Amino acid sequence: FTSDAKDKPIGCSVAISTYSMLGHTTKRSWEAERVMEWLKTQEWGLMILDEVHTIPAKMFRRVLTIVQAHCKLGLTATLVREDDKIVDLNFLIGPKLYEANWMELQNNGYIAKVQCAEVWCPMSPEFYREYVAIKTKKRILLYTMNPNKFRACQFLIKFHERRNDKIIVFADNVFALKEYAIRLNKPYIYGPTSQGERMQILQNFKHNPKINTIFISKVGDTSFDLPEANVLIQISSHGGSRRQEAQRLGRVLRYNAFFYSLVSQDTQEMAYSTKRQRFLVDQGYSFKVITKLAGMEEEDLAFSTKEEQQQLLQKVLAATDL
Amino acid sequence: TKRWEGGYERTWEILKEDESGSLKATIEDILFKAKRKRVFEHHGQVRLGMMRHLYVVVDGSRTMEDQDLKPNRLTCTLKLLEYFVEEYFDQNPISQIGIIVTKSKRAEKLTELSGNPRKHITSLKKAVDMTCHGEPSLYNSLSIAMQTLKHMPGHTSREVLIIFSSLTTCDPSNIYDLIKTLKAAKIRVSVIGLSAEVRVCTVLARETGGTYHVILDESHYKELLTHHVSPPPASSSSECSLIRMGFPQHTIASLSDQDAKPSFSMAHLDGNTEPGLTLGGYFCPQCRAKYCELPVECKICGLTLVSAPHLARSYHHLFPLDAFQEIPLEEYNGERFCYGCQGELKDQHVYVCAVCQNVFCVDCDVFVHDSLHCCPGCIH
Amino acid sequence: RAVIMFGVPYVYTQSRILKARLEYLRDQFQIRENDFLTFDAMRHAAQCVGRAIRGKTDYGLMVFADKRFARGDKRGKLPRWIQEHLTDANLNLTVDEGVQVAKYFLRQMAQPFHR
Amino acid sequence: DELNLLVIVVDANPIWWGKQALKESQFTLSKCIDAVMVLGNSHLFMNRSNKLAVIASHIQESRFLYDGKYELLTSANEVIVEEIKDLMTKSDIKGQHTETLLAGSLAKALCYIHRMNKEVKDNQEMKSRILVIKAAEDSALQYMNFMNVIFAAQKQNILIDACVLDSDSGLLQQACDITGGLYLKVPQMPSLLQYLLWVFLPDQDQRSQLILPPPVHVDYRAACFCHRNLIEIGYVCSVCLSIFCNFSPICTTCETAF
Amino acid sequence: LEEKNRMLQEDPVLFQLYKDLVVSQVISAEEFWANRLATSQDIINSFQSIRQEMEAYTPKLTQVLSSSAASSTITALSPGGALMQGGTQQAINQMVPNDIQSELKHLYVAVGELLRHFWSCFPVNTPFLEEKVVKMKSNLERFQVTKLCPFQEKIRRQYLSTNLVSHIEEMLQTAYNKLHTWQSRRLMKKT
Amino acid sequence: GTSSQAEAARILAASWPQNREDEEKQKLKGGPKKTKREKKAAASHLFPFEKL
Ligand SMILES: [Zn+2]
Ligand SMILES: [Zn+2]
Ligand SMILES: [Zn+2]
Ligand SMILES: [Zn+2]
Ligand SMILES: [Zn+2]
């Protein structure tokens, strides 16, 4: 029941739908209205909720009260959430039943032993002056488009492609991701592209040796059907969302694999990365700090000279969204 | 009903206290039970074997140029074949390997059927830079293998392994007649394909008694090769099967004695470069021919030169060590020192051999059953 | 193992026999001419493509070499036992990705299964 | 953190030492025991954590032998002297057996090394080697057990060093070659201690630094099942890999296996 | 003739061997291409004597080693010593010049081929093979006289310290002894 | 520019966390390796791109 095929939801044993449709605050579709009227007239056994962590919302909570069910079973992988609304989930649904021990889970070999990495790059002088000069929230793009971080990401991409490893590159701030992906001429998901284009890109991502690296803009921050990947490189993620980082780490496991996080020194990204890894260290993961990359000057990388690095300043300051 | 819908398991009920501190006995028991996690057998599978004349058929068609396995099928196949040859010669002392390459509707015998590991590896390394052209011909390769293995002794297990990458084979004649002839020749044929299932390969494997498999990835390829490494089970007694083979002692030469006699190696004489005229090596017990590598069949008199330790390494399977009788320490009225390690016996259980009636601790018993394979007391 | 449909099989409109039946269905059973033509085409396509699966152990590949099959009005005419296996991921993919999908499917279907 | 374990196996066959004493030569069993004790004391002096074990092989069985000088050495030497005196004084010839039970002593040494390995703290690795001094002639009746011991030592990565005095032993040469140990024949018996300190005293890592005599011509003659004698050419079964000196219509071992 | 000549031209080494065997009258051309196509109670007395001798045992220090013994042991273990023999064909890669080395390799190949033929003939199960082994022995002797004797003379003239001929003599002597033993058995079987 | 490559490499490669690590490396590594197991531990904890 998602207003896409309408496979006669009336008179069904198991019904599968999504949020934001059972709690509509506006006028509803006639067929959808009739389906909801039918659905609100009978009891439900074992109402299953997915991604329960984002249950305590303004409209998602009343979804529990808008339908009647006997048992409410919630499933999630990242129970961590800000705004301390997880306590509300104790009485909204029930108590925390089971919490898997990830360390012993990966010790059995059924979960990939991901070697977590936290490697930072120094801020180029052409960028740090502008970073310390501006404070009105325009510095988000500055450390995001750090030339040193760009070189590190390109080096990691090339190294892992040379050994035939599937790579997923997470990157928020899709504006930066545009010039981050078109520079290397690699597929990227802007996010409001289409439904078909994303599906075919992800479908040909796995069974193709020619292309094995993609860029994602906050779209992979949920439970999707992304294929198996061994390398994850996140750049300029959200502020302090431990849930987002835990989900991104969850997209790799299924040292079989390893994921890297790139941050800029002497910036808010350092504090953000420090405060958003406290969930995984409680889970047992340790983030090794990498300050030097072997063979950085062995091959040619982008932004080799200062000319294009200083040219990047004009285009990164060209936003002027006022 | 369901197993998980009944009562919740309470595993912590095992531990109990009676003297406010007896948990030490329980944890000691747990530690004692943690040991002896093996079946006292390093392999636990086939306890014997039989001489195998294995032929490996390698596709050389354009399909080997595909990049399914990095960098291409041919290179990964050759690397895994080198590993397979090494492991197979390690686990089979008197076996032989031949290599046939199929290309352009023809079959070429790349290497003769022999037991030398270095020659096969050298040929495989040379074959890395070959040219992949044409289409494979299973009929010709099987005909060559049958012709070579037709005259082999019956007691030897004749096996043929085919690595079929291309899905199409060109047969100059009917192939099912050849399959029937192979069945009459008692030749085992196994096929490991790469792309998909092929009807002819499955029929051939089923009729010849072999196994047909399809590769999922490089790890599955290696697993299939390792499975093929193990020798097949052998009957208790077949015939008067024996073989005249020598045991060349590794006699080196020193200039201190007057018998310092340099000699060119027979294997090195065929090389383009200057053969190594070393001081000494392995001299044939029959015709005093000099060889550097073992096991190598003698070129002159045809004798087989094998290393005695290689043959003797599998002798423990013939006479496995009987499991020792577990007896509690209190019930044993004798010495409280282990006969093997001279350590004091403090464990709750003491193991006594049925032959010499000695005392061995848990660690010494595990060491004897796993590695030593012989009772120290029985030796005396 | 593979059944290929080169285009939607449409009966020839000539001989002035199909058009008479179309007119009769239009003025009698209120059947749209395009709807009936699509129904006949998809019925023939499914009949000639569903003969590759006879028995539980049997397996096969089915491909349609026409973008017109991509429209929902023709996909909906396929039998239900084939609809659920036709994911939205592969509805307009090119030849190379179709070949890759076929390779993966055949590679993964060769392993032993139990009864 | 480098722990070295030295297990010294002493060929205490009474017959060979009695013949040597009757020869009235400059070398006796007492001098051999003194040299072994000095070598053990030097090994203990090499490092604090070094551990020493001494096993003497006899026709009967294997005996665990273990003022101005070191206290621990004084205690160690006295215990070894007492043990060897007890073994020799109570050594009574009862039977026709003359060959030394070398294999059993090696098995006991392997068991002792395995026991000591577990007691070692996990942060340290106990590199263990076995030194054997050979006086009597080699025994071919224990070929299978000797090969099993060699294979176990190779599996556990234990060096085996042989110091042949009078008669060369092929089994010791095979053990040294397989386990990577050193095989040396003593030219002058009274100088035995100098050879032991010059060659067998340093550890394997030190052997890489030092220059050592090349290995002697190691033989690999096999032992027939029905003769237990060294052979150059023999018949070998294709099923159980048993070795026979003469052709047989049926394999005796395969006949046993049903 | 034309077919036979082309085979020799393609392999000059075989052509050299063909001349060294056919022109030198060692073998006939017909046979050349045919193949191509303890004691008493004194022991107990000694055991008792050593038992009594070691019954009263006292450790010694000075008698264990001496300066002369240590010096002799070091000299033996010094480089160039008995156990540390450093010669071991010092420059055999450059000793016995490669002109002789090529001839030595050719002689090795010829002897190996002849012995391979001899051992293929062995064992002799038919009276036909009896003459063939005699012919092989005659060919071996002719080849030895034709080549090895001048080879030995050249080695003696140049005074090469390596006993290259010794291994070749060992194989030939072994083959001759085996043939003589088999002939002796054949005579015994007829008795 | 030829000099631009060198200038950018000098600035980037050793900006913050190399001007003190290189000094410590130059003022250290005088004694030999304590044990070979340290190299094994380093190889096990090092990422694949730091092994080449
Ligand atoms: Zn030979
Ligand atoms: Zn014990
Ligand atoms: Zn026993
Ligand atoms: Zn025998
Ligand atoms: Zn047998």
Image (spheres, coloured by chain):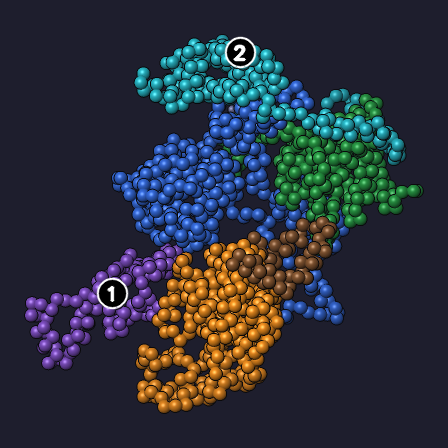
Chain colours: A orange, B blue, C purple, D green, E cyan, F brown
**Which mark identifies residue E150?**
2
Q: Quadrant of residue A152?
A: bottom right
The x and y percentages for residue F38 are 67, 53
Where disc 2 sits, the SS reads helix
**Which mark identifies residue C66?**
1
User: How many callouts does the rendering have?
Assistant: 2
Where disc 1 sits, the SS reads loop
Residue placed most toward the observer, B111 or B145: B111
The x and y percentages for residue E115 are 48, 19
Residue positioned 48% across, 83% down in the render: A322
Residue positioned 58% across, 40% down in the render: B316
Chain bearing tag 2 is E
Q: Amino acid at mark 2?
A: Pro
Compared to residue E140, the image places residue A207 above or below, namely below
Tell me if mark 1 has few (under 14), some (14-19) or many (20+) residues whose alpha carbon lies within 10 angstroms of its own. few
- 1 and 2 marks in contact (CB < 8 Å): no
Direction from residue F41 to residue B86 in the image, left or right: left
Residue positioned 70% across, 31% down in the render: D213
Tell me if mark 2 has few (under 14), some (14-19) or many (20+) residues whose alpha carbon lies within 10 angstroms of its own. few
Foreground disc of the pair 1, 2: 2
Q: Do circles 1 and 2 both sit on a common chain?
A: no
Compared to residue D47, the image places residue F6 above or below, namely below
